[PDB]
Structures are given as structure tokens and as C-alpha cells.
Length: 261
Length: 264
Image (cartoon, rainbow over all chains, first blue to last red; front, side):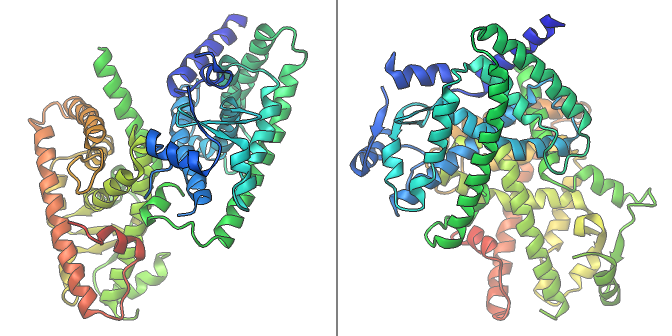
């Protein structure tokens, strides 16, 4: 039965490598610099960034702050398809009621986005467009209200999350645990969701004990980060509402709005 | 073999996403139309009195032709939203230039709507209100001009298209092929779209061979139907230009207005 959890851990790792092109391992090599990304530290470097590197997130289709915000949304929609593909590789997931599969992804993708975004962040900035770019924390903070404090909470979360020093093999199982949450609203058959998560939690616990034997109660500490993630998502939703209500320059092509709803 | 295996995985992925995106499948539509059951029986609207009773029996301007026309607008906007949700699930679609995403949906959505409207149709009429209702082909043709001419060419297409006997698993890949069309006016990067469609076309070819082994050149026959769809759009566009001018008191939903703005 111990061999079964190690097999599940390996399976999830291999699937995570297939689904997510920019791994934490690769992201960290770039951030520390064991290899070079184009740095966006102000408006002039942003302009040169667009011009030279052609970020599909920033492509013209207007105020810089809004074009950065909309770039974040375009990337978020990309990430949802990578996560959806990963979810299908989790043993039991495809066998669930199809409405429940949709429900788990609907409520799970935000938590997963901010988990995996930590992998691309240090205290100084964030890797963008598959590690070709590095946007500074200070530059994001300098954006006019309310866009100035849109990324800052993610940075504060990331710095603390990154202190757990998890690797891709740890994260693969943690992300699977997040997807198989039996407390999501509107679920029809909670039992086989909790049975799969119970199995993933067992796999995650062995993985952290074998991978991080010196790291006392790392399992407990990682599960506590669920609190930090759900608060980040609740907080982010509350910022979207403020934006939709008080900003008059957010409008895109109506089909564009539908895609990136 | 490994090549085949990847195309079956893609087929399975697209069918799963199709069931998740489209609440009323062909399988459910046929079960309602073939009227075998006691629980799935639709209320049938064939005249003005039947329509007026339908208003109560089913859960949804004054003039009858207009109420139907604007009801059809609301549903068409809802279908656009479902098709947009489906498009995002097509591997590679959300990774394309954002302008090309908008362009592919702009030209793709109505071709898909008419393809999928075939599923809700037999030679005698069309399912409405998530299959709770059935509106007869005769009632729709009897409507004051030019409103009587909107649905007839859709029915004509549907009776021919339905003779191919496609199921939802076939249709999931076919509508994917329609969206990823490299020949849409004003596409910026044609190559990556063609590369996705080539893989989708390989997936469709295998799907039809395995699912319809006795159906000779079904692949070729299905691809030729994309000619009929383009044709339905052209006629529809011309018919809307007439309404715009004759009914100055009537409003076209902004999303549809945008889709048709500078179309061809």
C-alpha cells in the first residue's frame, strides 16, 4: 500500500510536467539566474518589452494599468486549460459525475493559479510570458489605484509560500488535493471526491516526509496555506467587483469579454 | 498505434467538453422528437392560440412575428456564449493571438449555430425552450414577411445534414474544425490555426471511420456541408438588413450586431 502512494506521486509528477510547460525548477533557475529574461521596471522598459518580445498578453487590440490587468486575465484563461488537462490525469477524476468535474474546476482554478504563480515569484518580481519577461514588484505597485495593490497580496502570499521550499513533485500532489475539495458549492456526489482526496492527502504526506524529512510538520503547514489561498481568492473577487463598478475604460470587443468572462 | 491513440484522446477530450458546454445534446433532442417516452413530451405550437397557451405552459414587442424573432435572438446570444465556452476547451485555441480568437468566433459562431440547430430539427419543426416546446415548420413559414423566410433554409439544410446520421461525438470534432478555419478574413497568424485544424481533421477522419464504418466517404460528404453553412449565413445577413430598415422600432442584441458588423 506504501508502494501505491509512491506510484500515484510519480504519476501526478509526470502528468504535471506534461501539462505545465514552465516548472518551478525552471522558474527558479531563471529567477536566481543559473542559465536571460527581459526586465520591465518602468513605462519605457514596458514599451521596449512589447516592441521587442511581443507579449501576446499586451498585444494592442489605452492606459498601461488596464492593459497589464487585461494581460493577467488573458494568461489566467490559458492557465485554466493547463489545469483542466492536469485534472483529467488525477485517478478517479474523469469517472466523477460530469457536473461535479465542472464544479471542482470552476471553484479550484483560482486557488491553483495563485499556488503556481508563487513558483514564478520572488520578493522582487514575477516571470511573465513563459519566463521571457520579469516584471518588478515595485513597477506593479506603482500602477495608479486600484491596480497598484492587485498583485501585491499575491507577492506577500508567494514569499511566505516559497519559504516552505516545495518542489514540482510536492506541488503536483498539492494541486490535485485542491481540485478534489468536497466542500465546493453545488456538488451532487461528495463521497468519491473525498475518497480520492483522502488518497491524495495520504500520497502528499508520504511525499513530504520522504522529500523533506528534516521539515517538521510540513504537511500541517502546507494544509494551513489553504486559509491564505481562499482569502487571496475572496480578496481578488472583491477587487474585480470594485473595478467593474467604478472603472469606465475596461470595455473590450464583446466576443473578447465573453471569452475572458 | 501511438498516432491513432493521440487522435482518440483528442476525440474523447472534445466530446467530454461538448457535453459540459451544450445543455441540450442531439441524443436528448432525438429522444424528445422520437416521442417514445411519457416524461419528455414537448408542448407543440402550430398556431396563435397554441402559442398563447404555450406562454403559460413553458417557462421563458406585442406583434407575434416580433416576439418570436426577439425570443430567437435571446437563444442565439445564449448559444454564442455556449460555443465560446466550448472554443476555449479546444487545445491551442486560447494560446492563439487574442485578435485571431475574436476573428475565429466572429465568423465561426453562426456556422456552428446552424449545424447544431439541425440536432433540434426534423422535417416538421424545431425544439425550443430547452426541448420543453416544439414549434412547427408550417407555423414559422406562415409568419408575416420577411419573418416567414428566416427558418425555412435552416430546415432545408437540417433535413439533408441529419441524413448523415452524425451523433454528438462526431459533432464535437466537426464544430472544432469549423472554429479553427485559417481562411477567415483578417487573421494575423494563419499557420498555427491550420496546424490545429490539421490535427482536428485527422481526429474527425478517424472518428467517422471508427463510428460509421459502413458510411462511404462520410468525411468528404461532411466537409462539403461547410459550403451549405456559408450559404445560410449570407441569406440570413441579407434578411437582417431588410428588418433593420422595415422595423425601425425593433432592436438587434449588441453581441449579434457586433458579430455581423463588417462580416464579409
